[PDB]
Amino acid sequence: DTHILVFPFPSQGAINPLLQLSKRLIAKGIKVSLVTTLHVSNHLQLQGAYSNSVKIEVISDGSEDRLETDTMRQTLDRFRQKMTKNLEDFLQKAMVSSNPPKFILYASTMPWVLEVAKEFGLDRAPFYTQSCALNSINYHVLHGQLKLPPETPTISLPSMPLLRPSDLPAYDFDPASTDTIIDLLTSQYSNIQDANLLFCNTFDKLEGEIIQWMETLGRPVKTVGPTVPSAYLDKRVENDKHYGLSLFKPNEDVCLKWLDSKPSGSVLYVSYGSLVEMGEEQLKELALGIKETGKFFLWVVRDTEAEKLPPNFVESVAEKGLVVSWCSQLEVLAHPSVGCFFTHCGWNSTLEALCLGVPVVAFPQWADQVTNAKFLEDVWKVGKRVKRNEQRLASKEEVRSCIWEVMEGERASEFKSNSMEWKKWAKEAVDEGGSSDKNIEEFVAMLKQT
Image (cartoon, rainbow, N blue to C red; front, side, top):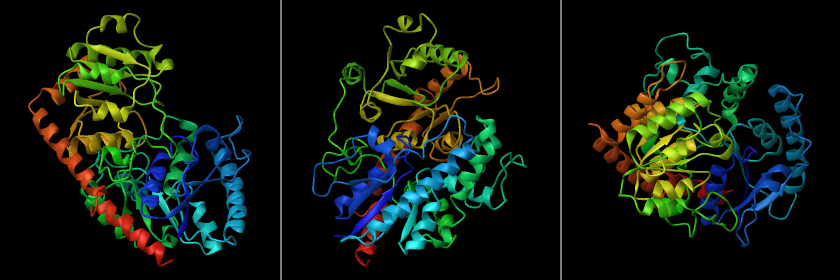
């Protein structure tokens, strides 16, 4: 049995892409151990019941955790110091065991793992879980060809679409942290000379020319995305309809029965994601903008955000609006009544929209979302960005008009056709003999040659 270790950044936000790739690997007969923290093991059920289930290895005791007195630099330094020792201690045992690991696939956000693997003579690769376009941007910031505030009105990087400063990641919503965050993101590319391979959560048809550019940095690049459950793509990995490793336990849902009663392609699904804390003022314009379309809509908004809705809003949209605390985003986007996704354009939501063939109204908030939104509008052409004026304030008119343009306007048919093509290509990539399948098969072959 060929045994590898997978080490995602140990946060609930960051682990799904490597768990999904792990399921593809176990389907091809690799034995996977997940290396993780006490915190992650305490919050997710990661243990499967089968012979080939991912093996969970908790390597920490929770002393690596953030303290309230920390700067982000102090938190990262402690996390790196303690988790370096924890991984060395784990490998000291694993590497002398009875079926030692032949490889460690780690989150690109933990570049220190490479130097541990180098000390032990263990083959290793980082996994870049965001777009390849962000790899180009961060690389160019590392090497001084691009700066945090663009020194130029337009940015033309090699093999990339033209970018405005407003198209570049905005890591400045946390002013004290901005330097620390840019240092972490640029450090992801500093030690790649010693990586066996670079893994990327994308597919060739989506970012082909940018993947070819990344191949010129001198290491083999393997596109293995999208990391969306098989059940929504190629359906070759039996019963995979959720992101996790354990028995899926479905919630009680109102959403799909409501959708069932609406016409095909009719309803706007709204989600600005589970981390964004939207201001009262922007929330009011968004709510009234959606209301002004007169379209059926399903808005999933968590309880601490719903508190900030205009007082009579939910009552005022009794007929057309279903405002709820939770739906399955995968089951909603896959529903035939859903015609459009009003999204913050996080990479995971971006890939889900592309995989499930749903046009977008892009409302990016922070970090890479603005770059994802630029590709969705200007490159992949599956929707439009909401126009913003008053220091990133979108008016109810700008919300309404954007929804109408994507769902009803001259380019609505174009967006739908383009969305259906990307869904086809995303399925093709992960299906037998597709670009991502071939890369995974090649990796598995390489692992068998030890």
